[PDB]
C-alpha cells in the first residue's frame, strides 16, 4: 500500500560539489515523493548514534569527522520498496562495484567520499527517520502523479 | 540491405509525464532512423487486437481501459537489432528490475505504468507496424549519416 | 487560455543532425502537453500549400526543395501562450540573431538551415494543424501535474 | 559584497509540478551558495505577513489561499549581486514576458501560478529571510570552488 | 565566409572547474568544426604577447600570473561567422552582464575569473591562431554533416 | 594509485556525431583532472604505430582508413583507477553489450563505429601517452576539489 519511506541525505563531498539538485531530481524522476527535507550540520554526537553499528571499526573516527565536516541535506522519500529501490538507485557503497548510471558510480570514485547515505533496511529506515527527524516534520500529502505511479 | 524495424508505443503515462522529447532523444543519439510516427487516442477495439494474445486474461479490460486513458505516440525505429536493441534501451518491463541508464529505470517506478512499449521480436514487431500504421505512413529515406553509423 | 495550440516542425536538417530529442524535451520540461506528433517526408505538394502564402516568393523554389529534402517531425503543442512562448523558445528567424537558451540559438548557424519552424500566429497555427493533421490525430488528455502548471 | 543574501521560494504550483530540483539547479549551477533550505506549508497569518504590503488587496484572500493551497520551498542564497541577479534567473513577474532561459520563461504560462518568488531588493531580502528563517538555520560554510568563483 | 576560424581558449579556472567537455560540446552542438586543440601551460612570454594590447595595464602582471597559474585548453573553431557567434555563445566580458545559456552566464560570476576567451575579430583570431597554434596542428577536414549545416 | 594517468582517444565518428563535449564533461564530473588534451587529423603513419601489433591482420587497413577518415581528440585523464574505472565509463568495446549510462552505451550502436577509446591496461596507457604526446604537453597543477574527491 505504498507505505514505506526512506531517509536520503547527501554527504558533504556531494553537497560541496553541487550535487544536491541532481540527487533530488533523480528521486523525483524515479517517481518518489518527498516527505521532509532540511540542511543541518550533523553534530559529532548525532553521526555517532547514526553510525552506531560502525562504532567499533578502525575507519570510524575518520568517517564521522568527515560526516560532520559540513552541512548535510537530510530527507525522507516515498515509494513502494523504496529502501531497496533507493539502495539500487544509489548503487554499491563502494562506488567501484557500482555501475555508471547509479549516482555513486557516476559522481564519486573512492569509498570514503561516496556522495550520499541511503538506508540499508526497513529497521534502518524507521531508526533513521526517528533520529534526524521530528514526527511533525514529515508532512503527509498527495503527489499529483500518484495514480499514474501506483495501481 | 533493409533493417529490422521496431514498434515502440509510448504509454499514456509517458506522454503525461512529459518525456516524449526525453524518450525520442534516446533512440536518436543512439543512431536509429525513425521511419514512422503519429500521436493517437488508441481505440479500445484497436487495443484489443494488440493484446489479442491475452484476450482470456482478467486484467484485460483494465489494460484496454488504462491504455486508453491518455494519448500514445505510436513509433517505428530502424537500426541493426533495433527490436532487441530498443528493448536494451528500454530496460526490463518491470521498472524496479530496470537498470538506470534506461528509459524505464530512469523515469518511472511501476510495471502497470512502465512509460513505453516495444515489440518483443521482429515477428511481433512486423505485425505491430502493419496494425497501427498505414504503409504510406512509413517514410523511406537515407540519413546523411548512414555511412558513419554503418560500414 | 490553456486550450490554445501551436505548430512546431523540426525541419529536414533538424532530424539529420539528430536534435529531435533535445527540442522535444524543452517543450516538455517547460510544461506544455504534446497533442499530435508524427514523422513525415512532405510531398512537394504538401510543402506547397504550407507555403502557398510564399508560392510567389523568389526563394519558393529553394524553400520547397529544402523542406522536401528530408523527413520531418510534425508537431502540435498545447497550453497557455504556447504560440508566442514556443516561437520565443525557438528564438529569432535567423539563428545568427537567436539567443543562448534557444533551439536555433544553441544548435544552428544559418537561416538556410534554421533547423525548425514555429507557428507565427494562431491563424497560421490552426491552419497548420488542420493542414498536417486530421482531428482523429489530436490526442486530448491531462497531465498529472497540469494542476501544478495551471490555476 | 560577496556575503549579500536573498530570499527565493518556489510556490505550490512548483513543488506539485516536480520542478524543485530544476529550480534549485539553475542557482547551484549558476554558482550561488545555499544558505538555508526548508519545505513548509506557510500558515494563514504567515502568508498574510509576507504580503502584509498587499493587505488592502482584492486578490489578497485568494493569494493567501493559493500560497497555502500547497507545500512551499523557502530558500536562502548568498553571493555578490545575488539579489539583482537571481531576479534575472527567475525572469519578470509575467511568465509570458519571462525570457527563454529564465525559470519563469522555461517553466510557466501565467502570473497567478508563476512557480517562484524572488527578493526584489536588498532591504526586502533581509526582511524576507528574518521573517521566514530562524537565526540558527542560516548555515555558514565554504564552497570548494569559492576561489574559482571569486577574485 | 563559411571558412572562417576563431580562437576560443578555456581559461585556468575553466580547466580547474570540470568544464572542458561541456565547453567543447557547446560549439559541437551549435554546428561548429574543431580545427585544432591542445592542453598546454601558456608561458609568461606567451601570455604577455597574446595580450600585448594589455602588457602595459595596471593589472598586467597579475593577469599573466593567473593565466599562467593553471593549464588552458587552446581551441580553434571553424565555421560561418564562428567569431561573431562564438563570443555570443560565450557571453559578455562581464559575467554579471552575461545572460542564461552563455558560457559565462551559466558557470561564472566575476570578470577576473571569466572561465573562457573568444576571438573578438577576424584579425584578432588569425593573430590568436598563428601566435598560439602551429601551421600543421590546424586540421583541414570536411564534416560528414556539413551539407546538413550549410547549403 | 592517485597519480595514475590513462589514455583516451575520441574516434572520427566521435567528433562528427557531436559528442566530444559529452565525453569530456563526463570525465570531469567524475573527479578527474585533465592532464593533456589535443586534436588532430592523424596520419596513417600514426595509426600504424598505435595499431602496430595488428599490422598483418586483414582488418588493419579499413581501420587505419577510418581512424584517418576524420579527426581525433586525444586526452590524458588523471585519477585513482582511471584506466580501470574509466573503461567502465566507456562501456564494453562492443557498444551492443554495453549497458546504457556508459559512453559507448549511450551513443554508439555498432562496434565498428564505437565513438571513443580508453586504455586497456597500465602498460598500454604509458605507451599511448608516449605516442600521442610529447612530455611537455602534460600539464601539472591541482584541481581545487582534490581534497574532496580524495581522503
Image (cartoon, coloured by chain):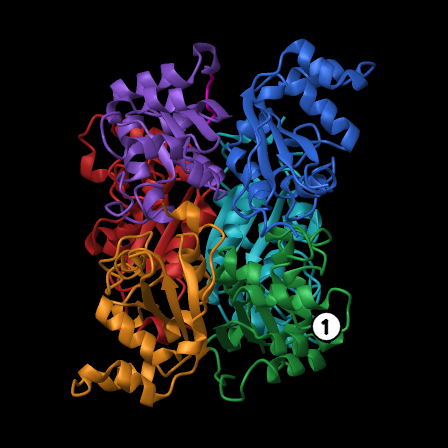
Chain colours: A purple, B red, C cyan, D blue, E green, F orange
Q: Does the rendering let one see residue A4?
A: no
* Residue at horizontal 22 percent and vertical 39 percent from the top: B52
Seen from the viewer's position, the closer of residues D86 and A2 is: D86
Q: Is residue E67 left or right of residue E94?
A: left
Q: Which residue is mark 1?
A: C57
Quadrant including the C terminus of chain A: top left
Check residue A144 for magenta coloring.
yes
Above or below, A131 relative to D117 = above
Quadrant including the N terminus of chain A: top left
Seen from the viewer's position, the closer of residues E71 and A18 is: E71
Instruction: Give SS at disc 1.
Output: loop
Seen from the viewer's position, the closer of residues C57 and A77 is: A77
Above or below, A14 relative to F103 = above
Q: Quadrant of residue C3?
A: top right
Seen from the viewer's position, the closer of residues E141 and C54 is: E141
Residue occupying the far right of the picture: D56
Above or below, A1 relative to B18 = above
Q: Position of residue E70 (x, y in %)?
A: 53, 64
* Residue at horizontal 50 percent and vertical 46 percent from the top: C36
Q: Position of residue A68 (x, y in %)?
A: 42, 30
Q: Which residues are magenta?
A: A141-145
* Residue at horizontal 54 percent and vertical 48 percent from the top: D145
Q: Quadrant of residue E121?
A: bottom right
Q: Does the rendering let one see residue C39?
A: yes
Q: Position of residue D150 (x, y in %)?
A: 64, 50
* Residue at horizontal 47 percent and vertical 56 percent from the top: F143
Above or below, C66 relative to A118 = below
Check residue A116 for magenta coloring.
no
Amino acid at each position: 500500500m505504498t507505505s514505506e519511506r526512506t531517509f536520503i541525505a547527501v554527504k558533504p563531498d556531494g553537497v560541496q560539489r553541487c550535487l544536491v539538485g541532481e540527487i533530488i531530481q533523480r528521486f523525483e524522476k524515479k517517481g518518489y515523493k518527498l516527505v521532509a527535507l532540511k540542511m543541518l550540520q550533523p553534530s559529532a554526537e548525532q553521526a555517532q548514534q547514526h553510525y552506531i553499528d560502525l562504532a567499533s571499526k578502525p575507519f570510524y573516527k575518520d568517517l564521522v569527522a568527515y560526516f560532520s565536516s559540513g552541512p548535510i541535506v537530510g530527507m525522507v522519500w516515498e515509494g513502494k520498496g523504496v529502501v531497496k529501490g533507493g539502495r539500487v538507485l544509489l548503487g554499491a557503497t563502494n562506488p567501484a562495484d557500482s555501475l555508471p548510471g547509479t549516482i555513486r558510480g557516476d559522481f564519486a570514485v573512492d569509498v570514503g567520499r561516496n556522495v550520499c547515505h541511503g538506508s540499508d533496511s526497513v529497521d534502518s529506515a524507521k531508526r533513521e527517520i526517528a533520529f534526524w527527524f521530528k514526527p511533525e516534520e514529515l508532512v503527509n500529502w498527495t503527489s499529483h502523479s500518484v495514480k499514474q505511479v501506483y495501481e
